[PDB]
Image: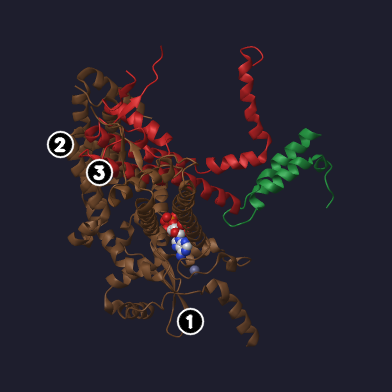
Amino acid sequence: GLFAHELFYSILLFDLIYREETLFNVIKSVTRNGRSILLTALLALILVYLFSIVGFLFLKDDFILEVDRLPDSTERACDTLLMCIVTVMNHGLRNGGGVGDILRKPSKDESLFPARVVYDLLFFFIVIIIVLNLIFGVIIDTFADLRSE
Amino acid sequence: EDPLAYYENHTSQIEIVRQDRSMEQIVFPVPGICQFLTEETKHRLFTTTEQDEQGSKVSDFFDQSSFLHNEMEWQRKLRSMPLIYWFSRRMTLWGSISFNLAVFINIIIAFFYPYMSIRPLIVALILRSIYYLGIGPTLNILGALNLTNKIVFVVSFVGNRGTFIRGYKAMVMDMEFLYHVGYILTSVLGLFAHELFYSILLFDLIYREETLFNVIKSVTRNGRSILLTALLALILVYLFSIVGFLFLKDDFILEVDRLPDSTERACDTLLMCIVTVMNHGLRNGGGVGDILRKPSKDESLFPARVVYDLLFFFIVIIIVLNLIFGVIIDTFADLRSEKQKKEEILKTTCFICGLERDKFDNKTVSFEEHIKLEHNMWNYLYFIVLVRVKNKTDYTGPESYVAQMIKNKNLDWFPRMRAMSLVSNEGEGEQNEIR
Amino acid sequence: FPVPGICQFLTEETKHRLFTTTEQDEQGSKVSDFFDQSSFLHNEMEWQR
Ligand SMILES: Nc1ncnc2c1ncn2[C@@H]1O[C@H](COP(=O)(O)OP(=O)(O)OP(=O)(O)O)[C@@H](O)[C@H]1O
Ligand SMILES: [Zn+2]
């Protein structure tokens, strides 16, 4: 920080954790069972992979994302399986509704509308409602275990 | 080399209670067959037996004694066979190889599809194969290797576990064997039907890691409660959709991106309105109000819309969706408490008699010595095996009594809440003083 | 017994750390950890002097 660049001093802020015991305990609430959290994240990734496979096999067209290109306004994000997996894992996980929010809105006249509805409901109930809540439940359980100990 | 050492190794001691409720010590020779019991089965029996209603673990061990003897016989027979024994001894290696192959295959398909420690070394070899032969041939080779490793692993598993000893019906009953068969079928499908099927093998991670299995149990333990809560949410959504269709049909206007009007009414029919609510309102944080057309204060029904939106947000979204999470947290807490209680009982009590460790403090015989020598359960298993194998004409007094109790399906011969070292010395001293 | 002079050099922070850090063994006694740390405590007394 003194020589290389002034920004490096920001790292020293982490020393707060060392100084305060309460913050250290709060962090231990996560670090104590970090393996469980990582395994839950891997399970979420596997579920996202399966959902992306299903979408690429059947729902390739609906994966249209608007792009603000620097100086077409939409792009297909399911041409390749890897790109579809990335799009799902990013948008669906970062969106409260799920992957359905980014997907093109279907019309009741469309023959595949019930399939889209079922897919969106399954993704919301499985990937978002449970696993993301499972991580929080693990954190709460770790808190309780630490307090009891 | 040392006669005393050999005699000590092959001699066991147990404690029994006669019909007169008097403790007695029996010293017997260890049957040779008992030497064939594997350590994995011993650990499984120790860490799996569950306390009965009375709180004693004796009944489960007595029930499993026969299966333990059969497993000893099977292990001796297997040891008679060198190659099959060697294959069985390395089941974990085969499982690890299969898991790594499946993970690498899944990574390759995910990264490249559509197309057309030693682990770093395997990764380098796989990368070289991909660069040289291409994605297709490398995936085919990896799938063939995975299939071969899986058949070897299944053979080793059936050999080591000896589930066939119980019976073919028993082997079919076992869930692990069926899971392995399904894994083999999925691997075959991936090799032949389509490369995507290999993704299913990723689920094997749950089987490999115990922490992930416990996390999933956090949901599976009370899945019925979660499903009933979801059904209650569906009923509430149905009632809200009925109300909306009866009164708020117009506000249900949804924009649609038709493939090559920009808005459509989604409440013309009750079923369509129910679907629209159950999808958008549940998937939207705000609730059903977010999709509904924005009302204007000038409109006469604006207060009704405000009340409807607030009720939907406070009832359907705030509570029920939070009720599911609360159920999950409660299940987590219950599982943690159960595990803690089981661990404490296992590490602070005697398996055979249930006496607490604190009872043995400040005494000649410590709890560690008591469990190790005086009240070892493996000694009881060996004695049961000896009684079964030994000829009736050669039965001694205590052996005859134990055989009669076993035949009569009785279990009082096991000592319960009684240790000779604990109280016999003090009782003898008191009796001497009284005399 | 008489208290050795070296023992007077033990610092209070180390005493508090030992009291609040020792963990019960399998038998449930804290004696073993204190016995193990006795040598380090003596060395710390020498260093403090
Ligand atoms: N009745 C019992 N109550 C509690 N723990 C028990 C009981 N019987 C056995 N154990 C424990 O189960 C394990 C079995 O002990 P065991 O005597 O088989 O040990 P080992 O070292 O494998 O044997 P050895 O060295 O005598 O060949 C040990 O952890 C022992 O403490
Ligand atoms: Zn005992």
Which residue sits at x=56%, y=51%?
Answer: A144
Give the residue drawn at x 62%, y 53%: C24
Q: Which image quarter is the C terminus of chain B in?
A: bottom right
Quick check: B186 left or right of B325? left
Q: Position of residue B366 (x, y in %)?
A: 57, 63
Chain B shown in which color?
A: brown
- Tell me the crowding category of disc 3: few under 14, some 14 to 19, or many 20 or more residues within 10 angstroms, Cα based: some
Position above or below: B376 against A108: below
Q: Quadrant of ligand 1?
A: bottom left
Q: Nearer the viewer, residue B303 or B89?
A: B303
The red chain is A
The percent coordinates of residue A82 (x first, y second) are 30, 27
Residue at the left extreme?
B192
Read off the residue under disc 2.
B193
Mark 1: which amino acid?
A: Ser
Chain containing mark 1:
B
Q: Chain of mark 3?
A: A
Task: Identify which residue, B124 or B87, lies in the foreground.
Answer: B124
Which subunit holds the residue at mark 2? B
Q: Is residue A64 visible?
A: yes
Which label belongs to residue A114?
3
Q: Colour of chain C?
A: green
> Which label belongs to residue B22?
1
User: How far is mark 2 from mark 1, CA to CA?
Assistant: 70 Å
Residue B434 left/right relative to B380: right
Is B198 situated left or right of B22 in this image? Answer: left
Nearer-the-camera pick, B231 or B24: B231
Q: CA–CA distance between discs 1 and 3?
A: 75 Å
